[PDB]
Structures are given as C-alpha cells and as structure tokens.
Image (cartoon, rainbow over all chains, first blue to last red; front, side, top):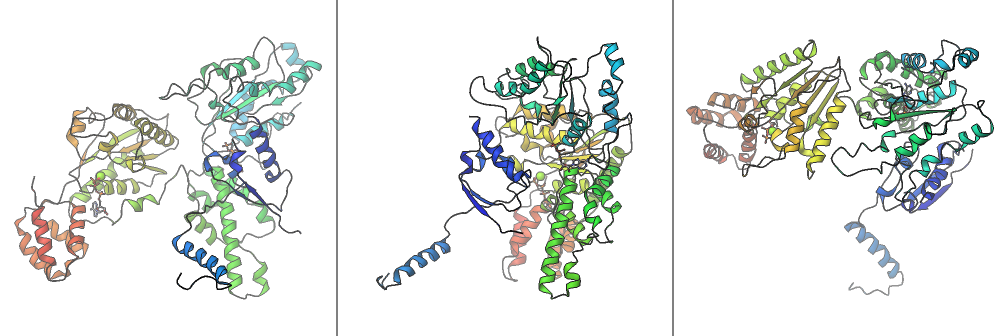
Length: 98
Length: 534
Ligand SMILES: Nc1ncnc2c1ncn2[C@@H]1O[C@H](COP(=O)(O)OP(=O)(O)OP(=O)(O)O)[C@@H](O)[C@H]1O
Ligand SMILES: Nc1ncnc2c1ncn2[C@@H]1O[C@H](COP(=O)(O)OP(=O)(O)O)[C@@H](O)[C@H]1O
Ligand SMILES: [Mg+2]
C-alpha cells in the first residue's frame, strides 16, 4: 500500500537508436519489465520523433497507450488569448477598444 | 540421466504442442539420454543446433526455453536479430563475436566436463546475403554470416554449445547455414486446431477459477469452436479484454446504482462480456475480417430480375467443387461486364456466402502512390498468408488498375503482369485448397495479353436491358411515390434502356433535389440524355 510516483521524461527518441543506445534502453527496460517488480511507476514521457523510438518500448506492458497534441485550435487560441488578456485586465490597464 | 525416457510437456506452459515435443526429442536429442558409457564407447558427436519456423506469435520461444531448461542447462542468453547491425565498418561482427566468450573460457579451463549454453537467436534471417536477390539494394555486407559460421565450426572446436534459431520466412535463409555439422534439423509450428484452442483457454483461465471469480454461466467448449484460426497470443488478449470489460462494467453499474455491498464485492464477469469483447474488441490476423464488407456492400443487393440468381448459383457450384474434391485443389473464375454494373458487390457476396475460415480482399485502394515492386511484394505476401489455412478465398478487386493500363500507348507494368500470371498457376502445399475470384471491365485486353488462358471459367454480369426490369428495380428500391411511377411506366415502355445500377442510384438521388413538380421531368430528361445503346 503506497502512493504513485510520477517520473516525467523528455526526448526519449534521442537515446533510442554507438553501442550505448542498446545498453541504455535495456537498462531502462529492466525495471518496468518485472524483474524489479515495481508496482508504483507512472512514466509519462515526451518525444517528437515517433519513428526513432524502439517499438519494444511500446510492446504490450511497456508504453501501451499513446496520444499527440495538435494545433492550438481556433477556439482554443481564443481561450488562451482570453486568459492572458484577463490576467492583463486584472488591473484594467488594457484599453476597452481592444 | 537428463530426463525420463517419456519426457513431459503439459500443464506447466506449452499448450496445444505435444506431438512436436516427442518428434523433436526422438529425432535429434537422443544422444543425451542414453547411458554415458555407451555414448563414449561408440564415439559419436552431438547435434549443434535446430531451426523452428512458422507463423508469428504461435508459441515458439516458450518451446525453446522449455527445451533449454529440461536439459539441465545454464540460463539462456537471448538476443534479437536486427539489433546486431551497425553502420561502422567491422562492428556488426564484433557483436557476433561477443556471445561465445564465456563458453570459450569455460571450455578453456575445464575441458570435456562443461555444461551446456543455449544462445537462442531471433529473426535469424536479418543477417543473410540472400535478401538482396529480391528487387532492391540491401546487401547486408555478406561478412556477418561468415563470422558466425567460422565460430560454430572452425579450426578451433567447441563441444559445449547448442544454437537454436527462429524465423518467420523460411525462404530467405542462406544455404550455407543448413549443411551437416551446422543447424541441421528443421521443424514447423503450425496454427492450433480445436484441441489446442481448448487446452490454451483452460490454461490461461485457471487463476480466476481458483477463487470462483468466474461465473458458472461461461463455458469453454463454445468459445473453443467459435475462435477459428486464432493464434495463442490472440486468445490471451481475448481473455485480458474480457477481464477489463467486465471490470469496467461492474464499476460503472455499481457506481450508478447504489447496490448493496453483496453484489458490490462480487465481480462476476458472466458470458456477455466474453461475447461482447470477442465480437467488438479482438480482430484476428489469419481469419475473416467482418468489418470491410460493409464498405463494399453499401446498399444491400436487390433482385431486379433473373441474372442475379444465375450468377449466385454458379458461384455456389464453384465453391462446392473446390471444397470437397481432390485431383484439383486450385480453382479460378473471372467476372466481367460493362462499367458501373456492380461487379465488386457480387464478388463480395459470393465470397461471404462460402463460410470459409480465411477470406481476404486485395484491392488497389490501399496502394496509392506505390512503386510497382511494392505492389508485387504486397500481392506475394497476401498469397503467402493465404497458403497457411486449410481453406481460403482471395479476391482481386480490379485487374485493369493493378497493371496501370492506359489506352494511349498502350502502356503498363510488366512485372505485376508476370507475377500474377505465375501466381495464378501455383498449387498450395499438399492437402490444402484455395479459390480465386477476379474482376474487370475490359475483357478484350486481358484476352489479348494471353491472360484469359490461365483462368478456368468466366461469368457475365449483364446490364439492365428492358423497361420492365427498370420498373421492377425502381419498385423494389421504393421511390417516386407510385403515382409518378405510372407516368414513368408509360414513358419507358420503349424498352430501349441501357443503364447501370450504380448510375441509376446516382440519377435517382440527383433528381430528388427539386420540388415535387419538376422532379419527374428532370429524371426523364436525365435518363434520355444518358440513353446510349450497345
Ligand atoms: N443487384 C445488385 N448488384 C450489384 N450492386 C448492387 C445491386 N443492388 C444494389 N447494388 C449496389 O450497387 C453498388 C455496386 O457498385 P460497384 O461498386 O460494385 O460498381 P462497379 O461496376 O464494380 O464499379 P467500377 O467499374 O467503377 O469499379 C453498391 O452500392 C451495391 O450496394
Ligand atoms: N501453445 C501456447 N500455449 C499457451 N500460451 C501460448 C502458446 N503459444 C503462445 N502463447 C502465448 O504467446 C506468448 C509468446 O509468444 P511467442 O511464441 O514468443 O511469439 P514469437 O513466436 O513471435 O516469439 C506468450 O505470452 C504465451 O502466453
Ligand atoms: Mg469495379
């Protein structure tokens, strides 16, 4: 009985690909594989090159589910601009004409 | 001794593979069970490897680990094929060298008393100077497979190794790697039949039975006769998906309804979850794909007259001939007709009504922008997959577009034509059947390219040729409110109507875009304008 630890990683594609890559990837895989049996592992990672990452990292039980973030969205762009300009209006410095 | 003479392979692992074990152990490893004294007196050497091939994910590595353990061997040293390959010069071979070190040292200090080391490979075909024969430029050095051979059997001899290799494509394995003294015993791991699909299911669901989590509703014989050509990994995924869906259902239901704790603890999965997941979640790879039919038979099949029944009956007769006859295990047929006459839908229906285990459709919609060699590779892969089932049915969607035919010139690709012409006359391995259905709109061109001599029969898909047939089709399609239909019947009594069904659908839909006044005249004008005759 314990809480969940959330370890964030960025740019996994760089390491996944001169013999250092294989050993590093295997060392990372060792813990999640099940030998170290860690049942408290939330590994939310980030990357920009889905084609330069080992598919073993996404083998069932490794990464499983994935998602991508798209354009800022026209309505989402409106919402973010609204948030920033509301922070601005917090002191009413912004002119009403805008 | 290393094992009792009768061995044992069950209930601890391997499922439907029991004959395989006895076969392999009687053929090859008979030199490690006989009393050592007679083995020494005879003076015989032991085999130095074996090869296993078959479909992907059918239970090969499990057998390798079991055979390694049951010989009283050290821990296996697994390694993957494509991973040992580097762009640097002379570094794809150091990786191969770095796997025999410990065995070398142990043989060095202790001679003729060491144990056994198993060096299980995987995708052994990646390193081979034979993939370059197929169109392309991938030479893979051809030095890699000269550093592995020189270590197994060279000037220096090792007598404490056993190399086991696995591959999916047995036709790209270099020939220098199968002579006596090297990998020298082949073996096949096929798809699991009924008894295997029963044993695997029983094995994979014992835990949930132990605690009575499973309800008494679910059986296993029913689920062992519905899953046709499933591979074991698919069965495991099916069980996992059933568990997950039942869990989600129970949490959602008990949350929405403030049920008493009695059913809240209870997490029975029942059988509804099993069927739901089976019919909605898991999609086999060597079985029927019931989803894509809805993308071809979009508006059902209407019986506007006589020809439909004739075509369907002929298809039934050919299916029956291919099912239950010998001396003729390969059968072909060709459907042809004028454009927009509905040739693809009839082919899909004929294929679907066969109830075969393996059904596949090879259409050009998924080869946009492909180079011709890619088309050849895709066709060959589909046929190879079709060769691995007792009964099969492969459809070719449009033969005039696969060749890139264009009336100017004429021009087309020769490679695809020759590949198809060779593939139409190649019998499958002994004891297996097949059926091929073509489709095209230009019979004369295929007749001219000497292609109509390879097919075994032909069927004609006629067009709407009389006013009465058009009237019946319109009546069954249910439009024009039956009062404008009287005027239509009066107008179309000429009997000089030559139109296709798909074009008829398009024309009706287009004419239905006006007010009730001008609709009939617009439709009649459109029909008259497009009223070209043979
Ligand atoms: N009796 C029928 N036979 C065939 N198709 C029918 C019939 N009744 C309705 N249809 C509908 O007609 C359409 C069949 O058109 P299809 O795509 O097969 O045309 P095609 O002649 O193969 O086309 P193309 O030559 O351009 O490749 C589908 O919508 C099918 O639902
Ligand atoms: N005969 C079988 N009985 C039980 N499980 C099996 C069987 N064959 C395969 N499996 C399952 O498949 C997985 C192993 O697949 P594997 O045979 O290693 O694929 P590959 O041949 O590509 O290496 C295991 O999780 C195992 O549970
Ligand atoms: Mg067509």
